[PDB]
Image (tube, protein in one colour):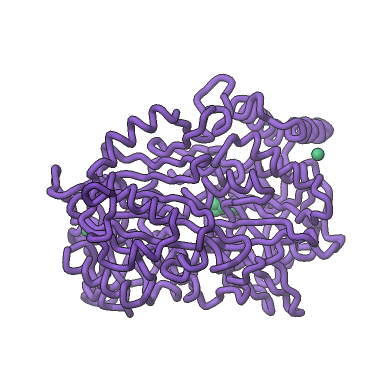
Length: 610
Ligand SMILES: O=C(O)c1ncccc1S
Ligand SMILES: [Cl-]
Ligand SMILES: [Mn+2]
Ligand SMILES: [Mn+2]
Ligand code: NA
């Protein structure tokens, strides 16, 4: 070198550039050159590092300690920066069609592509000098149990201590990961809040962000994730959606596995027999509630493996093995109660970071639907830091908690070979037409059932399509994703799990729920379990198998109207098939696989014979 080269050794405040794997050092030093951080901190993952970082954020006004609990914290954000922004989330590939199908008549709802050239301009308009005056933290992290053959490693560079703390909870991170990685391949994750010092614009609520320039980008062919201007959740904790669904789904396709928006639970019947099930419901639905269910049926146990993302690969015996690539739960707070989710309420009482919830005057947390009366003189500060009376919490407010703290965490939740999935459940909120539960007729049918998923949006009401619960998350062309799932039927040895669809939301003509739900949903899981064992507990219908009369355990429920709850109307299903047809034709178009068109035609045909 003729001067100091591009050596940032002088600016390292923890760790050593010399001890990094060569390619990790290149990634760090290149981005230090580009972003111009004041310091580089190579994270170790230690409790001391974590404790110190939290104390520091506290000193800078960035988080508040919640004094009601053991080591819990609260962040309140700039209200411009509160959620994933789909319209600023993009995937870059040489060809648009590889990322999203070319729709027939409308705009695609299945992803957003950006050209390499357009992304380069965007990147150049954002990242140069963006970390000036700030520490660049280097977060080495594993998605999956450390050293599992199903795990994948990333390195996230960030200028946000809040991301570092949250990534500690949500991933495995620190020195052990760098040691596991060695000279292997990793996903390159670059994040900045986009507020270099000295600040050009007002800092709101001690929450650095750059809303106008917010851009969450994915470069699967480069194995890169590049995210600018949001400090929040799925935009900044790059392991979760960006890596573990978007990038990972593309890797899965290359490699023969599946990366999916599914909870994983273990269910044990009164005789001690255990199965694992995976379930995909829209983000707005109760995946966490199901994954941590407290079953009402005596002798049944539910244990949680994960509440969000599943990586699944057929092993050499044909079993579908699943891991939770996450290390925590990043759960939507509102609606979490002792009634809807007692085990979640337990988990979050220790060592948890909350974002955009309300705070009680006794240093506790609160939100819509917490269903917990407040003591005599206890008042509320809203998530906007103002006094509040009976929203107090933002609808996308969150808890971020260690998975190991769940009182019903599955004993195998970190087993490196994964847990054997025997059923895959799809579901959506449908106030009419759709039965409580049905079973797919075949693998191909089951893939169609995934494809056809629809759900009532939270509020007049709209019923939206959300195939496989993956609509915001596909890493590549959804047609090709469907072909990938279909291909599993031709894999030698593969034991294809049974596929089900559920709906907890069916209403009578007065708008009253026909099914009580919550822990009563264990009655549906019981039926599934028996069907997997080969029990003759099903009746054939045009849409699939439903429970026979008297097959569902209704003991304890009184008079459940199973007649209406399992009613199938020709008129409803005629309309439903037409809406699914028009949707797949438009959105998937030339990339719709033959077998999915065949399943659509077959369902139309069975409905025609009613
Ligand atoms: O809330 C519902 O009723 C529901 N049921 C099944 C699957 C997803 C949801 S959101
Ligand atoms: Cl989010
Ligand atoms: Mn999710
Ligand atoms: Mn086939
Ligand atoms: Na704040």
